View 1 (cartoon, rainbow over the protein chains, first blue to last red):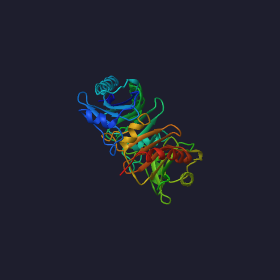
View 2 (cartoon, rainbow over the protein chains, first blue to last red):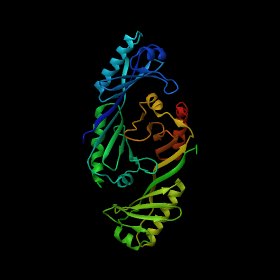
View 3 (cartoon, one colour):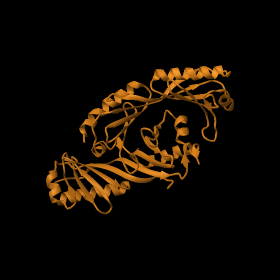
View 4 (cartoon, chains in turn cyan, red):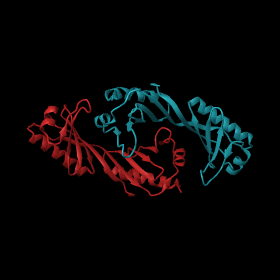
Length: 178
Length: 179
């Protein structure tokens, strides 16, 4: 709807121990390792639907969560799974790296008007990329603004920055209604 | 090719006088004003191909130029056109606001690898937008990185930042080459 909805949360954790990727893939019910295709073990859990990328270094990336809470729960679940597989991993330094979200203002935007009114903040070159790219400074967020009125907000580390960025941009969007 | 080529330069200038947009469009050989379509006069010159957006406020935006030099020359030409039309405009505070450029590294990139290695700097969600968006801090540039190996750099105010950004990213790109 009009309030940004979290579409993806990406987190990292350090397992604090080197893992044998081939062996995790062999023993785990839902994990694969194909180094020519991706240089990490790819492990997935059902509900909620998330994906863990488990690197040889011990670093783990968790993606696919729809909230900070779900992200933390997921990371804990993968840790548990890895421990039950018999590796000596620990849960260390969980951190949210990125939050992507979206909303829909339900009217069309004249992107050309917005771009030339704020050219030091955004780029619009439909020959090269669809939609208008707006680099907000306070807070540090990149917004993708589409003619349809769909808005994507990227680069947030906490949810409050997403809402604040959308509060900042909204009065600008209404000025360029199509 | 491999070194970024400037694709667009956007600049602004303050004319220092409120202009009658309807009258500029009437008198100018190649300018139009349709306030329901765009809230500015759109004026265009042939060679080199550029566009001026002339606002009632007196502010002018010049777009379409391929270099800083060509942008300033275009601005000068539009000013001189406006002056010959009988308006009292002056050339105040020309400023480059944005430079967009592109290059091609001529290999494919595994965008998933790049995104999960550097998730605090970039976003990749092909369901929502094509290509990977990388927010560089030093210098302040946003790069769009595509599977094809095409790279777009946006947000630069001087061309040196474009080259520096690309020099910064290139060693990361090579780490994620794909067949």
